[PDB]
Image (cartoon, helix red, strand yellow):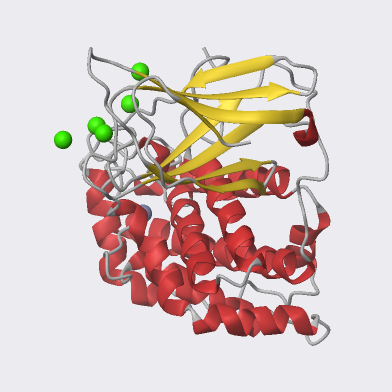
Amino acid sequence: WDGKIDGTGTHAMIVTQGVSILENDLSKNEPESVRKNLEILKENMHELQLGSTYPDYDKNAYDLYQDHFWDPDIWYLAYSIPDTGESQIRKFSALARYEWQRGNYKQATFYLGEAMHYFGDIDTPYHPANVTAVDSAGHVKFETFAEERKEQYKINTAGCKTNEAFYTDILKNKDFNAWSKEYARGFAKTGKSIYYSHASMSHSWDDWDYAAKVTLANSQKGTAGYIYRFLHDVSEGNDPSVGKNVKELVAYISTSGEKDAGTDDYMYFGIKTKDGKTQEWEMDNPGNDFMTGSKDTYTFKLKDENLKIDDIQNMWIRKRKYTAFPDAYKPENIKIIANGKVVVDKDINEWISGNSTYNIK
Ligand SMILES: [Ca+2]
Ligand SMILES: [Ca+2]
Ligand SMILES: [Ca+2]
Ligand SMILES: [Ca+2]
Ligand SMILES: [Ca+2]
Ligand SMILES: [Zn+2]
């Protein structure tokens, strides 16, 4: 969907409607904690909207915004694996719950907004069909069409109250990651079907009208559902990581904005377990890694699929010179996420020169 850097446009409408919908649908028996957290959410509507649009304007975005795409119908032992729209929902959702728990509500809500940007995208027709703006003139055309008419596509209810099926189903599965993937898959498959049936360049103005109606309604309802899940999760301190093989680790790395803080050297993330086994991956995204001021995400798939988070005793990042000279690197902060939970939040704010290793854990 379209969005503007000031937190306006289709994406902002979707999150804004998401909140209104939830407000309308909230049953009387909902816990006080949920209502209290919803009011805090509403205090930070600006952030939610800005977050819902930001990934399109992130200076660090990948070349063809690959991570804004996801096909719902779809070597890793030593290299990071790329993010997808689905995986970014999970990443930002984890960051959001983490910040919420420590009362850092403005930043928490921004992250929630970013999670919803990606959900919004996988609920378009073009993104889950994996048809890019390069592939088809229809990509930009359809999103512009929707943007112009976004007002007439707003909805204000999911169609039932939160003590009913749609919403109760959302709370059933304590495994947020597993729930999010399949929940997102449903909406994405609908969007993709709508691409082929109504939204592609083969179709009419009437077809595009129906396509936008259904996918914008679904985007809003789907967003309301994620917000509901979020308010419940943060109200109860629900941990979806318990607990639970660590099949993947995600690193979320903030590079300092200081001069020459970024690097083009080889960069590795590694772990050592209590049993002294090691695994190390090169961090390399389909993009310009470790740019000054950037926030980079890397996902690492473990060789041992039966490890528990406690089993991981040491973590580090290691740099290796690309040229004969040291390209010193200065990370501000690294967060490691496992199974939907931020398990490491490590301020660094010091230089890593040459071929040095920095010990996180
Ligand atoms: Ca540097
Ligand atoms: Ca320089
Ligand atoms: Ca490389
Ligand atoms: Ca790269
Ligand atoms: Ca660079
Ligand atoms: Zn979009």
